[PDB]
Structures are given as structure tokens and as C-alpha cells.
Amino acid sequence: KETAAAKFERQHMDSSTSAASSSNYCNQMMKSRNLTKDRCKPCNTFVHESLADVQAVCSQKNVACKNGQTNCYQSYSTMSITDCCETGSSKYPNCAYKTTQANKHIIVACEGNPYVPVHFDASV
């Protein structure tokens, strides 16, 4: 099956490009990463940093997870990200998104061996 770590990468990683210099970015990425298959995932964040740099966050600032668990970590620095959220008219199966570029500290849930990101908790 798809591992939790693999899912995090498919849903949230995009090192392949430094940014989303296109209004079509989210529509294309949400679609290609299968985030529009059975429903339009409302909002989703893509991180534009190397997978290695994101994985390194798992040994950075230990902070509470949204659910109160102890395995979340916040990046010391802000990271380049793209926030994708449905437009007002977006209605499954015709998902449509608004692309917003930003730079924020990210918080990820980590697990396993190797200890890696398995959930994108939030960006602050």
C-alpha cells in the first residue's frame, strides 16, 4: 500500500519547482497528485523545498500537533509554499483552485524509521 510517508510526499511535496508562477499551478497539481479524484480536497499546501530539507524539520522545533500529540515539529525558518484552495464556484467533479504563493514556517507530524514527515499539520 502507499505508506504514510509516501502519501505526505504525493500530497505536499513539490521541489521540482521553486514556486507556482502560474494561476494554473494548483489546478494542475491538485489534479496530477490525485487530490481531485473522488472529491475536491478543499485546500492543500505544496512545499517548494528539497525533500531533504523538509525531512530535516523532523529534528527541529518540537511543538504540539493540532490534535495534541507529541510528534509534530515546526521548521526554524519559513519555507516557500503554495496554498491551493477551491474557488467559490468549484464543485466536484469540476474542481477549480486559487493559487497563492507564500513563505511560512511549516509544522509536520513525523513518524517511523527513518523518522520522517507523515502529515502536514499547519503553516504558521
Image: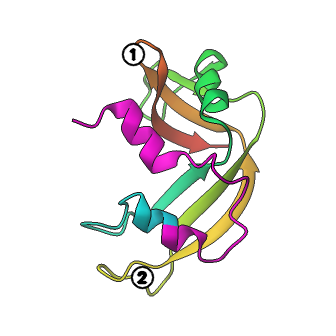
Dot 2 corresponds to which residue? 90
Q: Relative to 100, is 49 above or below?
A: above
Disc 1 to disc 2, C-alpha distance: 37 Å
Label 1 SS = loop
Q: Residue at x 49, y 23 (%)?
A: 116
Residue 21 appears left or right of 107: right
Is residue 5 within the magenta segment? yes
Q: Residue at x 78, y 33 (%)?
A: 77
Label 1: how many residues lie within 10 Å, few (<14), some (14-19) or many (20+)?
A: few
Label 2: how many residues lie within 10 Å, few (<14), some (14-19) or many (20+)?
A: some
Q: Relative to 66, is 42 above or below?
A: below
Which quadrant of the structure image shows residue 37? bottom left
**Amino acid type, residue under disc 1 in the picture:** Gly
Q: Relative to 53, is 7 above or below?
A: below
Label 2 SS = loop
Pick the quarter of the image with the N terminus.
Answer: top left
The residues colored magenta run 1-28
Residue projecting furthest to the bottom? 89
Q: Which mark is residue 72?
A: none
**Amino acid type, residue under disc 2 in the picture:** Ser
Is residue 15 within the magenta segment? yes
Mark in the foreground, 1 or 2: 1
Residue 2 position in % (x across, y down) = 28, 37
Q: Residue at x 37, y 41 (%)?
A: 7
Instruction: Give 7 or 59, whichever is nearer the viewer.
Output: 7
Pick the quarter of the image with the C terminus.
Answer: top right
Residue projecting furthest to the front? 16
Q: Which mark is residue 112?
A: 1
Which quadrant of the structure image shows residue 83? bottom right
